[PDB]
Every structure is written in C-alpha cells, then in structure tokens.
Amino acid sequence: MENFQKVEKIGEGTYGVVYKARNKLTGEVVALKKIVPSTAIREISLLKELNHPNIVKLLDVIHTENKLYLVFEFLHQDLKKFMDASALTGIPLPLIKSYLFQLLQGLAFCHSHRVLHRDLKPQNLLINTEGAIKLADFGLARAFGVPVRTYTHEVVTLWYRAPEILLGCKYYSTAVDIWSLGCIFAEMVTRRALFPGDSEIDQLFRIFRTLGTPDEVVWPGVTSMPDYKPSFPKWARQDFSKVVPPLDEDGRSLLSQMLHYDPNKRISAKAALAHPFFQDVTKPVPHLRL
Ligand SMILES: Nc1ncnc2c1ncn2[C@@H]1O[C@H](COP(=O)(O)OP(=O)(O)OP(=O)(O)O)[C@@H](O)[C@H]1O
Ligand SMILES: [Mg+2]
Image (cartoon, rainbow, N blue to C red):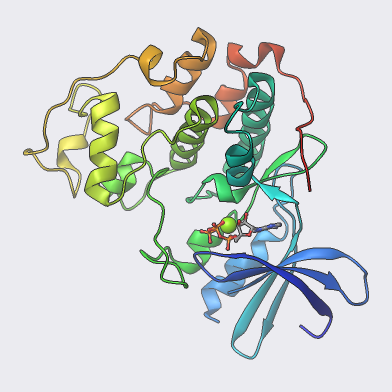
C-alpha cells in the first residue's frame, strides 16, 4: 500500500471497500479493492491471466499482513449509474445492443476457460467514454464465498440470480451468468429491474409470475431440486411482448432463450453472439459526463 495514494472512496461492496488510487511510482490511476485463506490467493492469482478487453483488468494482487488488496484497471462509471442518468430518455437501443454484444464476448471468453462470474449485476459492469463495457469482479465469488450481507452489512442483491441457484442447485453452470445478463438486458430496455426480489422467495415468486411456475415439462428435474416445494403457487407464463414492450422480435427471441428455465437449454454466450439480434450491431459512444 505505500506505493498507492488513495484519491477517493468509490464505494463498498460484498467483499470490501473500493478506492480510486494513484500508483506513486508507475503514475497509473487504478481502482484499489481492500478485501488470507490459501485457496483464495491461488484462485485470485489465476484471474490475473484471464485477460480480455471486455473483462476489467486485474493488474496486481497485494497480500500483506492478513489483508488482501486487489488492484484493478479504473473505469469511470458503472452501469447502474449510467442507467440512473439515462432514466428520462433510456439508453438508445444501438448502445444497449453494443453493450450486450460486448458483455457476451466477455462471457464466452471466461466460459470457454470454465470460469463463471456468479454475481453479474449493473454495479459490476463498467463503461468508458469510447463505448466499451467490461465485467468487473469476475471470479471473486468463487474465490471468497458470497455472503447474505455485504462487509458493510448491506444486502445482497438477488435481482439477477438464476432460478437453479434459488432452487438450491449446488453445482450450477456458466448458464447462471447468461440468466443474469438477460435480466440486465431487460432492465436497460425498460428502465425498470425485471425481477426486483427482496427475499429469496420473493425473487423466485417474481420469476414464476412472469415466466410461469416451472414444472417437469419445461424443466426436467425441477420438482426434485432441493428447495423445490409442490406447494409453490402455479402461475401462468406471460408474453415477452408485455414484459419488455419496446423490444423488437429479434431482441425478444434472444431474451427468452437467455431466460430459459432449464440451464442446459438456456443459450450459451457463444450461440447468443450468433443470434440475428446482432446483425446490425455497431459501437456507439455514450453521452458520458465525468
Ligand atoms: N475497477 C473499477 N473501476 C472503477 N470503479 C470501480 C471498479 N470496481 C468497482 N468500482 C465501483 O465501486 C463500487 C464498489 O464496487 P464493489 O465491487 O465493492 O461493490 P458492488 O460491485 O456493488 O458489489 P460486489 O462487491 O458484489 O461486487 C461499485 O459502484 C463499482 O461500480
Ligand atoms: Mg463489484
């Protein structure tokens, strides 16, 4: 830490506080996260080689006196803040599409190396002035554990959690990050979270009320999951024309496949990049005021 000057406190999250800092020798402006168990050091160290332009770069790992400091590339804004700033107008569709496309490329890269994010959400999607968007904190949930409250006792967002996780599947796949991104895609288009649950049962029941209570027809094996109960109410599925209205039929087809109940059938990131929705994809630059 003596090599870094804390410029400001950016925020705090699940695992610790994040500061904007300046490297006192390289001159570099970085984001410093102050979070050590053996398995986590090893796991965090492999993240250093998972480099991709749509993944926030992990520059260095500082393990000192029982404390762990992760040094990241710094981006000027997160997607929650961008959404809140664009609320009156909504993010134009071409930027939504470009962002979704780029995040899918990030996901196909990590997923092809068998690494899952596990906790995608707007705060973990960072943007710059050029039109790029990157996934932040990739791999940290597996490296450290995912607590019900943050280190600041603040609540864990359930809004983007895939239903297999909520139903108690222990070994879920890379399909959980596709569910999350699907949820974030719907939220960019409508300017409202898709499933804002405020407890596990609330989250699950918000899914069931839009997508229909899953059964053995749509998801073979669902009724035998750990937290599955035969007493769950039976709600009908709703039309995506009603769920994300402005979106065209390519968008709606892609989103429903990203929200498939059965994780084995949900589209993978690589097939999603070939969907017809991305046929006219471009890379606009956002209106960003730093
Ligand atoms: N590399 C980074 N560059 C710039 N700002 C960042 C960076 N990483 C995190 N921040 C921002 O700082 C704030 C704190 O992030 P942090 O990761 O602690 O919590 P979170 O993303 O909301 O939750 P989680 O801890 O589960 O990731 C968030 O708004 C995040 O957007
Ligand atoms: Mg984060």
